Length: 222
Length: 162
Ligand SMILES: [Zn+2]
Figure 1: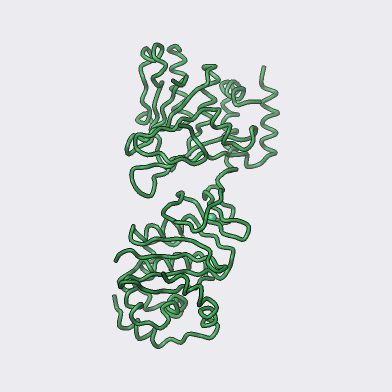
Figure 2: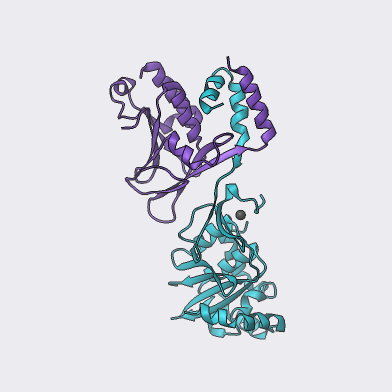
C-alpha cells in the first residue's frame, strides 16, 4: 500500500488517520559524519556531537539516543560571580592557569572563558582546561581525558551564545585527545581570588596530566 | 483544475500543516484554472516546527493525479512554501537557503532522500541560521514507534479498501 491509497481510505476513516500520524514519530535519519577540526559556528542547530573511535558524528537531537529528557549561559554567569565560594569544586579550572596571576586576572575580564568551562564541565567532569594569552587576550583549551565524547546540542547552542562572535570554538583531535579550543578574538573581586588560588596546592596526579600533555599543550599554543 | 478541487487542496493544506487562518495565502481559484504556473496557495512556515511535507505532497497527488511541486522560498526574513499542482534547485537531507533562493521539493526528491520506501514518512523543519537572514531546511524521515502497531494498522487498512 501507498500513501495514495491511505488518503482515499482516510477520507472515509479520519479515526485511522489520527492513529497513523501519531505512530510516525521515530526519526530514522538525522545522523551524519563530520570532519575534524570542527567549527561549532559552522554547524547545524539542535544537533549533538558524538566523538568516538568509531566515528565523528553530528546528530539532530530528535535523533539522539544518548541524552535523556541543562545549565544555561546565564546560569554559568551566576557561577562566575560566585566562583569565590566554589574554588575547591572548580580547582580543576584554576589548575589551568598554572599558578599565573596575570592569566587569572585576564579571566576576570573574560566571563565566556569561565562560562564555556562551566558549560562543558556540567556535561563532562573528565576534562582538563589549560589557559594562555596572546596580546592580553585569554585563550582556553579543554582537553578530554577520554576518547568517547558526547557534546549535547543544548551545551553547544549555549557555548555559542556565551561566545558572541568574539571567540572561536573548535573541536579537534590532537595527539590522541579530543580537545575543544576556545580562541578569543576580542574582549569583579580579583583580590581574594588571586590570594586563594595562590594559596591552593596543585597535586601530583594533576601535574602528571600536564606533564603527559606537555607537547599537546606546546602544539596548542600558536 | 476546478473550484471544489481548489477548496479541497486549500483546506487540506491548512489541516496537514496545522496552519492558522493568518498563515496561508490563496490565489484566486478563477485565476489558477487558467494559470497553472501560479501557485494554489502559499504557506507561512514557522521555524522549529515539524511540517508533514511528504504527507501533504501525496495528498495533492491523490486528488489531482498530477505530480505536485512545492517550493521553499527564503523571502528575506521568512520561509514560505509555495504549492503548485504542476511544475513550470532541489532538496537534500539538509539545505542552506539564503535570501531570494528557492528549493524545490517533489515526491521524486523525497524518494531519493528516504532510506526505505515503506513505513517511512518524511517531514521537514526550518531553523534560523547562526548569522545573516539565512534559514536551514532539514528533511527528516520518520518510522513507527512500534513496528507491531504499524503492521496491524496496515492489515486493518487493507481490510477497509473497497
Ligand atoms: Zn545528544
